[PDB]
Image 1 (cartoon, each protein chain N blue to C red):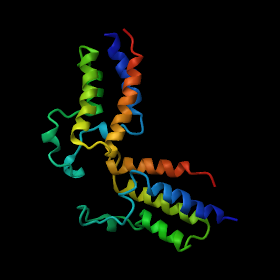
Image 2 (image 1 turned 180 degrees about the vertical axis):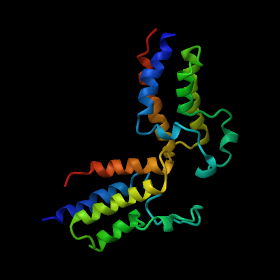
Image 3 (image 1 turned 30 degrees about the vertical axis):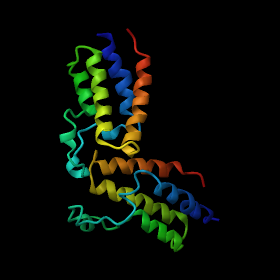
Image 4 (image 1 turned 120 degrees about the vertical axis):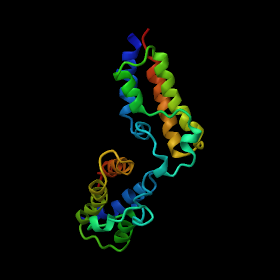
Length: 106
Length: 107
């Protein structure tokens, strides 16, 4: 049905994004204090990192993989909204977004 | 004369659009990246935007001056960093290209 797609995202995509050289600013929750950003959690109403995907797949929380992609994009869009064009964090995102989009197989 | 156009329209054009070229296009902010003693080690920092402006502003008198500015950039990175640091596998993969696109240069 629509659930063969859903473990593709777990066993292929998420695990291919995790071992990417750029995925470490997005692995865990943004530590707003140690990064001198005292607004990230007042600005971002939907904080999303990679470890939280991992667990909603482990937890089988996503019904219909549509719901799951939405969060992958939320993680890149969270980035683009907060930051600005050119920032190094943004070009790291624009290249993860690129590999993620390349995994349009099943 | 002739060659300086080539470095604009071929070498720099192709290097700029590579997947790895972006950490070399603008000055490194070692304050933020937390790189100790960066601009103390690197006497002469180099970015690709500077090679862009120098070719647009026609400051180079000879392609030699330009080619060294490229190598200054690569070598600058090899000095500060380890071999095997991801930034260096990037830098190396570029010089491999830089050298290919140079072996097809006119006279």
